[PDB]
Length: 188
Image (cartoon, rainbow, N blue to C red; front, side):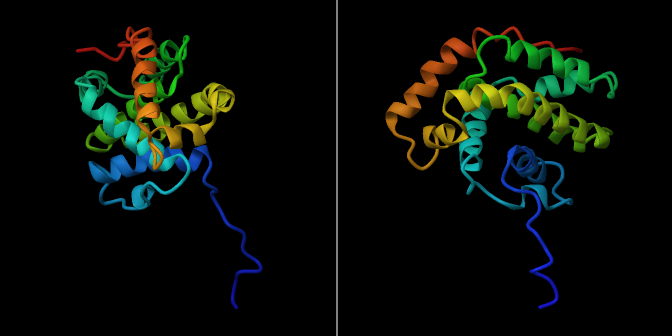
């Protein structure tokens, strides 16, 4: 054969692959459709199917998603990292539960979508790194000690039992509301 023995697999299903998945899938579905590739794969990984069900549920529950997206990019881009980092810290203040984990990725994924629809192409990768870095540096720790991404995949994945579902609901009740003041993206 031409290759194979001299070719190793690139990009494992790690956080980078997961962040590129959710954001890719979302962007590819509403913005970066021409750039088919990131969201070329569906929910099959032990985190993919988890985030997919998360975002979907939160996307339906969050009556304020694309608002802050416009609010931020209403004046001018670039200085979006400070806005993002502010709300991110407020989100990680004391409750990075799976209930909030949804909004964590959803915030950037939605942001990125509207960024590809506007003059914020380079900003997309920034939000992607701001997200993956904040996560890998602090979110991952909470996640690893809590139950892991696998726990989240069981919570709302194939084995999404009624107990796991009500668990997420009761969870976000105390966690998403305690950090509900992270609306620093709400500008004009």
